[PDB]
Amino acid sequence: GGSMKIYVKLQDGTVIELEVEPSDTILEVKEKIYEKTGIPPEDQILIYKGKVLEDSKTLADYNIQENDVLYLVRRLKSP
């Protein structure tokens, strides 16, 4: 259904690879990151082309395509 790989760079410099599809929402991308890292979605800020992404929009909304790189900033927030 348009399956593709995208990459997320962490603050420590490492890059993780995600399997996604264009209709995935940003919240769903954060859920995939949680599955790989343990970082709760509520503690994740995702950045693409210098802008913070909104949970309810999709990868296709942002024209995020195969091999694009997103940036993850982690929050330390009381649960």
Image (spheres, rainbow, N blue to C red):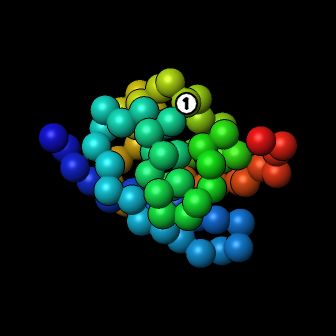
Residue 33 on image: x %, y %: 50, 55
Residue lying furthest front = 79
Q: Residue at x 55, y 30 (%)?
A: 55
Relative to residue 33, is residue 22 depicted above or below? above
Q: Is residue 6 above or below residue 28?
A: below
Q: Is residue 36 toward the left or the right of residue 22 in the image?
A: right
Within-10-Å neighbours for mark 1: few <14, some 14–19, many 20+: some
Residue 67 in the image: above or below residue 47: below
Which residue is rendered at x = 64% and y = 65% of the image? Answer: 10
Residue 21 visible, this orientation: yes
Left or right position of 51 against 1: right
Q: Indicate the amino acid at tag 1.
A: Asp
The residue most toward the left is 1
Q: Which residue does the image show at 52% across and 60% down from the upper left? A: 8
- Give the residue furthest to the top: 56
Give SS at disc 1: loop
From the viewer's perspective, tell me whether residue 51 is left or right of residue 63.
right
Total marks drawn?
A: 1
Foreground: 6 or 77?
77
**To which residue does mark 1 refer?**
55
The residue positioned 42% from the left and 33% from the top of the image is: 25
Quadrant assignment, res 66 = bottom left
User: Which one is nearer the viewer's eye here, 21 or 67?
Assistant: 21
Instruction: Specify the quadrant that holds the N terminus.
Output: top left
Image x and y of residue 42, in percent: 66, 40
- Residue situated in front as seen by the camera: 67 or 16: 16
Give the image location of residue 58, x and y in percent. Answer: 41, 30
